[PDB]
Amino acid sequence: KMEAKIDELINNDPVWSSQNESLISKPYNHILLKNFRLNLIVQINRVMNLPKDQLAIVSQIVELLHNSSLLIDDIEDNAPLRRGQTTSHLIFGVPSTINTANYMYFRAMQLVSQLTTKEPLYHNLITIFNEELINLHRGQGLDIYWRDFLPEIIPTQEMYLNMVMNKTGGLFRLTLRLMEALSPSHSLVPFINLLGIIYQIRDDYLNLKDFQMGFAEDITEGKLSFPIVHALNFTKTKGQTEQHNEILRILLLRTSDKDIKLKLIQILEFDTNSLAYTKNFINQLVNMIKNDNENKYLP
Amino acid sequence: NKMEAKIDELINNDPVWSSQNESLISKPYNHILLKRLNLIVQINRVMNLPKDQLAIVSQIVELLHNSSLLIDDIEDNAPLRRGQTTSHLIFGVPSTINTANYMYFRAMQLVSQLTTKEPLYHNLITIFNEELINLHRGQGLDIYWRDFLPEIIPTQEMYLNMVMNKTGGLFRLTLRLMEALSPSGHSLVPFINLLGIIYQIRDDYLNLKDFQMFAEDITEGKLSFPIVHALNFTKTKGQTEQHNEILRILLLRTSDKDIKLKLIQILEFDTNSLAYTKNFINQLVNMIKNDNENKYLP
Ligand SMILES: CCCCCCCCCCOc1ccc[n+](CC(P(=O)(O)O)P(=O)(O)O)c1
Ligand SMILES: CCCCCCCCCCOc1ccc[n+](CC(P(=O)(O)O)P(=O)(O)O)c1
Ligand SMILES: C=C(C)CCOP(=O)(O)OP(=O)(O)O
Ligand SMILES: [Mg+2]
Ligand SMILES: [Mg+2]
Ligand SMILES: [Mg+2]
Ligand SMILES: [Mg+2]
Image (tube, rainbow over the protein chains, first blue to last red):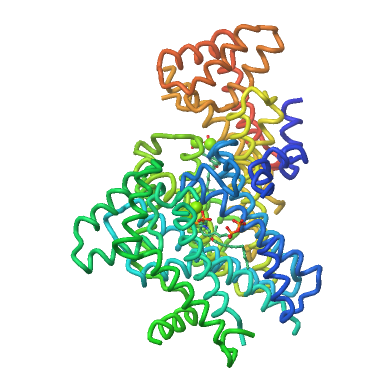
């Protein structure tokens, strides 16, 4: 009867129930308790005009990738909070959270084959998906390397921006490239690239500016953020050796101490003027769009 | 206007990625490489893929397998892998997670180097997508049972389905790709499933028996084949104290050798879970070694 049971098992597809599906989803469902990623999709479809069926799936794909990457990013950044709530790995544990997020990457991958049945086009959608997830990992990998090997390598603004094109551009380009390929209707990748860059620097700027006015978690993480990259390279360039070292020392403290975090912010405001330099950099990037009268980037 | 020219050129180019950056983030992966091909070769005696293709099927499987191990070691808190320190303890959990995941997608990339045939590619990618979804499901269950014990005490049946997913995942992936690429009998899938099952129960068994004679599965808290049998056997025979002591030890996440040895001797003399397992393994191997009407074997 034992041999019968095995015979049966090995001849069937692996058993997986609905209840099992729920167990594995808990870490992902928790972050869902968190519509502007979709506002941009909706808006771009005015150009692309994908039928609502196809569009919804693109939206589901983007949602799984976005959410999953955030679940793993918080494990990678040791973040206690996300969207004001406790992060999933602190509730379900790092193990289940890593596994559930990765599981969702593959669920997203599965949705990609339900956008089309056209074999040339299907290949294309997969290549896009594959190429941008590879790019998201390269950027994430470099962002983490610099942070965990600090002070071995201090990136420059250029190195930083190439990291951003990969890390933050990945999902923006993946979304748009999928829509342009599905479109039955100039490419907007340059503009989505510009948008993702503005997006990452704003995220890095706001993380510091909300605290000065915000937990300033980036400091606790030791992150080579945009204002930090500028402050470090500014002090190196002006010989401000002790400030250079003081910034490194605070980054390396992986501190949650309110006071010390404040000391580093005051270094960036009074000494290097990095926060004002970032606010300005952003504005410039936006102006590029606000003053695109020929519509070279804009549709 | 020079910065704008710089920004303009940036956004109009593919993202920049140097071979240097490629090495810096390959560290956790390069490390586990310092420590399969045979099963792929024997199986090919039947599928006859040309050597150019077989080598790619092989790089794919290596990438997926080593990546699975990197992640597995983080999820299981393993200090050792193949006699050496685990990558996460050297480079940190963050880099190891990201690199391991990076390699899953590199492996996916390679799939398109297997054929130009659009219909076939679509099937290769589906097989790849299905078995990785399966691996994750299995791993999900193994990890949930362990980390929330005793919310769920799995039965032998549940363990086996978890294994069909978890371990059968890569075995089936390897085999389904080959069957799909073959230029030349019945599917060898059931055989490959039985092999994944023997491989896992054997792994669980050897982890304890080699210590009895570091029993890291005890430290980890894994609902291993021997442990599932003991937990169910104890409840069934009404050995309340033993059932609870097994759980208590598992929940300690202990590295105390005497404590691990106590658990092992409990499965040895009190529940006869070790003998049950050894014999279950023998029976399974017997299913193949006595397959005279080649219902499993080719
Ligand atoms: C048009 C599609 C929009 C999709 C939703 C927005 C996608 C933003 C993608 C950002 O990608 C990453 C990559 C790596 C890490 N993160 C998380 C950041 P945070 O914790 O500050 O929110 P990070 O830790 O990189 O600062 C995000
Ligand atoms: C033709 C196939 C070539 C590859 C064969 C791979 C065989 C082993 C597959 C095991 O798959 C998994 C899945 C999940 C976790 N593990 C790691 C095991 P261990 O740490 O004991 O080595 P597990 O943690 O599941 O006991 C392994
Ligand atoms: C993780 C980064 C860098 C931004 C992702 O999008 P947003 O952070 O702005 O939106 P939600 O996290 O609230 O989904
Ligand atoms: Mg983060
Ligand atoms: Mg991050
Ligand atoms: Mg393990
Ligand atoms: Mg495991």
